[PDB]
Structure formats: C-alpha cells, structure tokens
Length: 446
Length: 53
Length: 101
Ligand SMILES: Nc1ncnc2c1ncn2[C@@H]1O[C@H](COP(=O)(O)OP(=O)(O)OP(=O)(O)O)[C@@H](O)[C@H]1O
Ligand SMILES: [Mg+2]
Image 1 (cartoon, protein in one colour):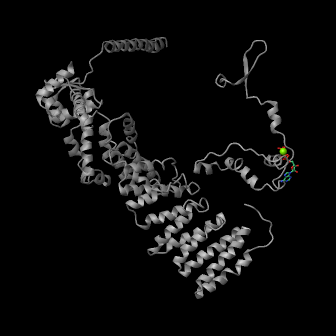
Image 2: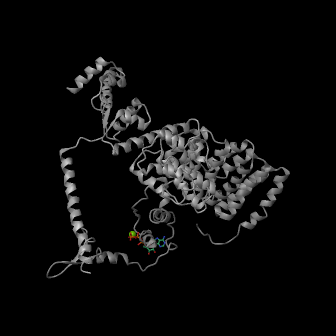
Image 3: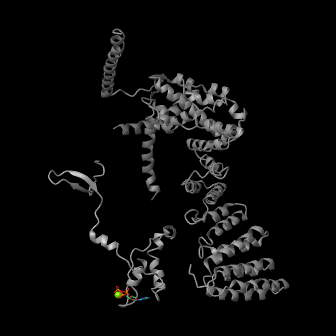
C-alpha cells in the first residue's frame, strides 16, 4: 500500500539469521529460537516489510513443526496474530503453511489444535487474505468426525456465497452443496430445501462438470422424492438427461429415459404436465425401449385402460428387463417402491375416470366399477375425492346408481352455443362459395 | 378455557364434515351419510333438518 | 415516435403551428456546465502535508464506496453520503478538496 523510499533491504539481515536459528532449535534450544525471532520481526513491523514479515512469520510456524512443540505451537500461533495488526497479508501466508500442517498430521490433537487456527482467523483479521483458508479449514473439521447430527451444525454455521464471496466459483458450488448432503443424512428436509435454493441462483457451470454439478445435484432427486413430488423430480432427471449429450454412455442414457418416462406418468394431470409429456414423447431416442409405448398409452386413443391388462403387459418394470435399473429403485423396493405402485394405480384409475367423463353423459355405478377395476364402494370413495377437490364434475344419485357428468345447462349457455353454431355456419357458407369461384369460375373459362 | 370451547368447535366441524360428504353426490340414503360420518341416524337426521332451515 | 414522449420529456415546438417536432435530452444549466469543467490546478496528494489521517478518512466516503461496493454489502452498512471539512481559517480544506478534484 504505502511505498516507503528504498534505503536498506532487510531481507539480507534475516537471510543469515533464520537458518542460524534452525541450528539452535535442532540441538534442543527450542525456547532460545522462539523468543529471539519475535524481537526480530517487531523491528520489521515498525518498518512494515511485507516480504520480510511474511518470511520470518512462517519460520516460527515452520520451526515449531519439526520441533514437535504442539503445546508451544498453539500458544505461538495466537501471539503472532494480534501483536500490532501484523501485516494483513503477513498473517495470510502464515495460515497457508499452517493449513498444510493439519491436512497431513494424523492423531487426535489435530482437532484439539485445529480449532485454534479456526479462532485465530474466526471472523476477525479475516477476508481475502485469510478468508478461503478458513473455508477449507472448517471442511476438515466436517470430515474430522465423518459426519453426524452435530457436524451438520458445524457446517451450516458457515454462510457460503454471501460471506465467502471472494473465492472460486467452482469450489463455492462444492461447499454450498456439500453441506446439503449433510442435511439429508440428519433427515432435516425443511432446511435442505432452503439451502438448496441458494445454489440454483446460477447455472451453466458445466465447463468441466463431468460430475461436479449435474451428476452431483442428484440430491434434489432424493430430497424432492420424499413427500409427494413427482413432476418436480421428473424435470430433474431430464436436466441430467442433457448430460447424456455430454456423457452419452450407452447404459447410463438408457436408465435415465426409463426414469424420465417412469413417473412422468406418476404426476397427476395438469396443464404443466400435458405439454411436458408431449416433449418427452416423440424423441428419436425413445424407440430403443418398449417403455415408449407405455407412455404412448397416455396420449392416443384416449386409452380406456384396464389395470389388469396394464400389469400383465408390463410386469417387467417391477422385476427385470433390458436394464431395469430404475425399475428396481422406482418400484422394486419394499416400502418406497410399493407406495409408487398404489400411486400408479391411482393415476391409471384417474385417467380412466377423466376420459370416461369426456365421452359419457350418464354412467351406471355398477359398470363404472368394472372399467375402473375397483369395488362399487371404492369407486364412490375415489369419485368423491376427485369431486371434493374440484377436479372432475360429477353428481351421483346413489339411490338409483346413476352418476351424470353433465353440468345443468344454463339458459344462456344453451343459447350461447346456438349463437356460435350460426357463426361457423355463416363463415363456412362464405368459404364454400369462395372455393366455388376458384374452381367453377376458373377452369370453365380456361 | 380451551376445554370450554371444544363443544362449539365440534359443532362447527360437524357442519363442515356434512358438507364434505353431501357435496360429492345428489339425493342419497341417510344411512350412508351416517356410515361415512360415523354417527347415529337419529342425530344426523335432525342435524340436517336444522341445516336446511 | 410517440413512445419516447413520456411526461417530463423536453420537446421542441414549431413557432407558428405549435407541434412537437423533436424530443430533446434534459437540459444542463450553463451554470452547472461551468460548475464541472473548472479545475486547472492539478494538485497532488503529496502537496497537502500534515493531513494524513484526514485524507484516509475522507477517501473512505468518496473512493472506497465507489470502487468496491461489495465490501459494504457484506457487513450490511450503507456507505456515508456527506462529509463536512471544518476547521480554523487557513488549514488545508480547499487544498484537500482540490486534491480529490
Ligand atoms: N498541508 C498543507 N500542505 C500545503 N499547503 C497547505 C497545507 N495546509 C494549508 N496549506 C496552504 O493553505 C493555502 C490555502 O488553503 P485552503 O484555501 O484550502 O484553506 P482554507 O482557508 O481553510 O479554505 P477555505 O476558506 O476555502 O474553506 C494553500 O495555498 C496552501 O499553500
Ligand atoms: Mg478556509
């Protein structure tokens, strides 16, 4: 910062001094090497020598390493960090050398003295000089005890991005997401969502992202899967499905599609899914698997499905198949997979009920059960659930077992439709005549 | 004091639960209302009578 | 165009049949123009002696907030707006101001 006029270079004075202190320490004069150095630096500090202060500062740190003076290392680390503000970058170099010490030295006291370096920086005498050094340093504590309930707190306390801004973007995404995996271990799902939203602020950092982000963002395919999310998880697999364009492994790409099409169907009907299913369908890469026609069973012919036929024609998605990799996870489990079996039946029953609504005015209750493949009492239970949620219009007269899907026609709606019929009829007449002139009055003259 | 207000809340909730069961259909046997509501036929009949007025 | 003629926009009008014929940039009062292109002195920080701590304090509200705004968004404070340089009649006040000028 401040450029002092060049009068005397202080490097030479320490050059012949630091190695001399090494000899005294080697013999066993651990103290004599220590106290002498501090007086050496203090003179440099008044002169505020960046290079001179840094080189000497590490030496005392370096010397204590080989000296095996762990008790004297910690006490020496503190005394060198709060004497006269030191030189801001001077402490920066010191932590770096001390940083490599923890990563290499095993045995318990590393953690005991590990926290000592954490507090030396803490959040005072910090920033670009000793900012990022802290981030890794707390990460080591994270792996200190392999990850537990307590560790999740030990890492959440670090507010990434907002505070550790002046540090590498690629490494940032790793730290921000690594604590997310800690959240899942403890099974804290509310916190996982909020922490998750802080990384999606920026995307498209896949320049060298073989697994850095895209394949490491699998957690959201685990967090979101917990409660009820199907469409949300579906969009995620497609998101990694762009990786096959980047990672086009034969087996990997095949399993992803089976997953994408698997519980795209699982999600309930909604305008968001209607255009999503269309995009998934029609790709020139879906024909490689029989699953394509299963998904096609939700688009064409209106597919009045028979759950008996669906199971018998597609029992492979529960045991085995071409690769069946998603099938074992999606449906092959004991509890998590089994739930998705009931949910699929609900969607298959939901498709039958909705489609029959379009093409039916009144359907007897008994025949409704046969199409839906559930008992009459169960059919009423499902119908009531849909009607109460304002999804399907249906009024059931259970005294006669007849349920009609027709809204009581309003006087204006009955007449309004008649108005629209005339408009089309008038327009067609205009179009019909205008097509006659193109033909009758063109070729005739010739 | 909370125990003082339970009686009102039970009356209020019973109102909502009856609508949730009668909305899904039209003319329906009262017996099935009792089975779904889990209540006797006598009180359900009267409760409906007060509701309609 | 009838989309840049928002309320407040300066517009020139014809002398005889008043009709907008051009949208204009906001005017600069000639006093304001003379208030900017003023200093020929070119005084350096090495001339204002004695005031060393004062300069560092003044530069903390003129230069720092206008070069590294992300620093103050960390702590959460909003950098100060004003600055009053008072003192005895004859110390360095106008000299210091011209220095930053
Ligand atoms: N530290 C200094 N180094 C050099 N010159 C100085 C210093 N302090 C004061 N001066 C002298 O002060 C003279 C006038 O200073 P200046 O007009 O800024 O002061 P002032 O009387 O307090 O200002 P004002 O009346 O405009 O508020 C300059 O010509 C300069 O030579
Ligand atoms: Mg003055």
